[PDB]
Image 1 (cartoon, chains in turn purple, green):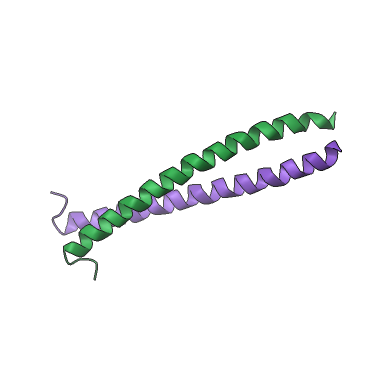
Image 2: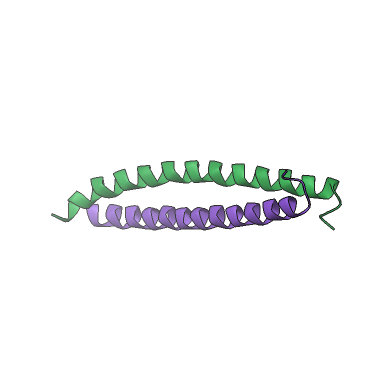
Length: 48
Length: 48
């Protein structure tokens, strides 16, 4: 009944919240990778 | 009673499922930028 429907909604909820946490962490790591590449470009005279 | 959780979880999960799509796009855009910077650095002798 409703108890089981609730449990399943909570499992889906945690799966979605975990994927969000992963994608926020992956986006942050990629912005750090972009900073590091841009700094290398700057140093080699490729960013003005 | 307990059943009021059903709507709350359903609605949260719709919001989270949408946010995952927006974060997937943000992550993909950052990956394309990293590929672009890697190629620039390679063309310029700087990626090994």
